[PDB]
Image (cartoon, coloured by chain):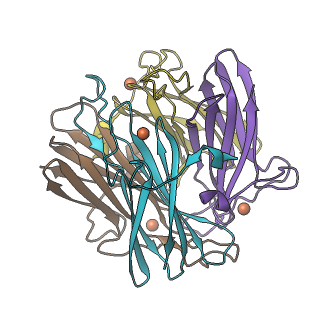
Chain colours: A purple, B yellow, C cyan, D brown
Amino acid sequence: MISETIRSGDWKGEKHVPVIEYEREGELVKVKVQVGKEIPHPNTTEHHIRYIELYFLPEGENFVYQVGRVEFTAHGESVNGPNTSDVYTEPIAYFVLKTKKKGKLYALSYCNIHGLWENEVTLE
Amino acid sequence: MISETIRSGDWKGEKHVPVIEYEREGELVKVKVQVGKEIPHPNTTEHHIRYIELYFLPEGENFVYQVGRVEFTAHGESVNGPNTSDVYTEPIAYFVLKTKKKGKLYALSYCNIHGLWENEVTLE
Amino acid sequence: MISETIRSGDWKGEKHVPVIEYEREGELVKVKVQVGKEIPHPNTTEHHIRYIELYFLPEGENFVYQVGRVEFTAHGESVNGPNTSDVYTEPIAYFVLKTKKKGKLYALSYCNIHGLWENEVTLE
Amino acid sequence: MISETIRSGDWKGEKHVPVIEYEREGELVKVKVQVGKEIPHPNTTEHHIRYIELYFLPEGENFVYQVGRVEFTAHGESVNGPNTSDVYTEPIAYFVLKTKKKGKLYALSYCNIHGLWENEVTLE
Ligand SMILES: [Fe+2]
Ligand SMILES: [Fe+2]
Ligand SMILES: [Fe+2]
Ligand SMILES: [Fe+2]
């Protein structure tokens, strides 16, 4: 099972845990997912969060839907060496989702050296 | 050249043109990119914006950096047919960039049936 | 846990399950992953495999590494309607990995209406 | 224009240019794209090819289709430091395209400190 490589936890003590927050405005659900809300995650050429993915499993349904994927692609690398570009993409992802359904939202994130991480929250 | 397949234009009359807006806060540059600001773009199983990419070429430098990529992966598809899931991901992308440099930001977006689209703005 | 949305099984019954095969040639490991090895998986505008990801957990290590990601982006869509372009990308992904380590390879695939699917094989 | 950040050239002299080769087997077009054919390209934590994308503009049509995208995500990074994992993903991408149409194929690749690179061949 691939799940044996996915870690979870308390984002209060664990900096890798993706934190999911949302604000439902009408038929629009604005979701914010970030890594390092309490404990800041490094963002260097050698160590950084590569991306965050958001999934949505509607209440009572059998198939999860991938809502979106955000890749953080700049990590200081340049022809002058690692951490010299002064260009870094922070692990903060925003998704605007249009739905009137309820269910569960899942976040899947990947650190280039610390593997896969997940979290979830109920979409009321 | 691939540029012969990339279209551009004024987003006040062309719904496909990605619109770039940003807010500088310290060393943090918050960028918002969206397709269909004025003229909303369809988002159906048959026709939808697939993703938006953000690039940054610092002033006076020779190599552009990809800042990030956002894929909008839900477009109504379900086992019950096209446009039946009530789950759609709107073409609105947000990027949090950490840099003190100035330059030019580029947005590249792709429609599943209307090809590639671009736009750019100066990052002051 | 996201694992509750991930399905698995024998590829001899479920035309979904991603099938992993590899050939080691020294330091080079060529991996082939595909969905629909037995009974072909549909590839229409309405129903298709979006991508296949390959992961590698070296023997005795604690963090899994994402080896690669292949997105199949053409599914017949065109300005003339769904399934009219005559351009389809088959769900067959190849990965050339350079490593002398052994361990476990995992494949994760996403169907646009049937959720996430996984499979794994030991890399000797 | 984003094209001002995209470089092109002779693959026999520039170890960055993506080389496109294909084979037509009836209805299937097997496309191989690689960076570093003539002059292998560094693949270190600090300097590596991030991905290769393949596009297809059918003869006489107005909209280019993205056929696929392959991300090479492992570049030696580990908790031990840069270039210590012994896990690297080579910049070799394979695409299986189902189409009876002819036209032009374009490859777009991104090095992490060298920007965007392109190439194109006629699909007969
Ligand atoms: Fe980490
Ligand atoms: Fe469109
Ligand atoms: Fe399916
Ligand atoms: Fe390079």
For residue D50, say whether it is visible.
yes
State the residue at coordinates (45%, 24%): B80
Whole-percent x, y for residue C67 in the image: 51, 64
Name the residue furthest front. Answer: C13
Query: On the rendered image, what quadrant is the N terminus of chain D found in?
Result: top left
State the residue at coordinates (31%, 38%): D65
Q: Quadrant of ligand 4?
A: bottom left
Name the residue furthest bottom. Answer: C26
For this view, does C102 lie left or right of residue D98? Answer: right
State whether residue D23 is above or below residue A62. below
State whether residue C69 is above or below residue B4. below
Q: Quadrant of residue A70?
A: top right
State the residue at coordinates (60%, 59%): A1
For this view, does D104 lie left or right of residue C60? Answer: left
State whether residue D39 is above or below residue B92. below
State whether residue B60 is above or below residue A103. below
Whole-percent x, y for residue B5 in the image: 30, 37
Whole-percent x, y for residue B41 in the image: 46, 20
For this view, does D61 lie left or right of residue C16? Answer: left
Q: Quadrant of residue A67?
A: top right
Q: Nearer the viewer, residue C54 or B51?
A: C54
For residue D116, say whether it is visible.
no
Q: Nearer the viewer, residue D59 or D14?
A: D59
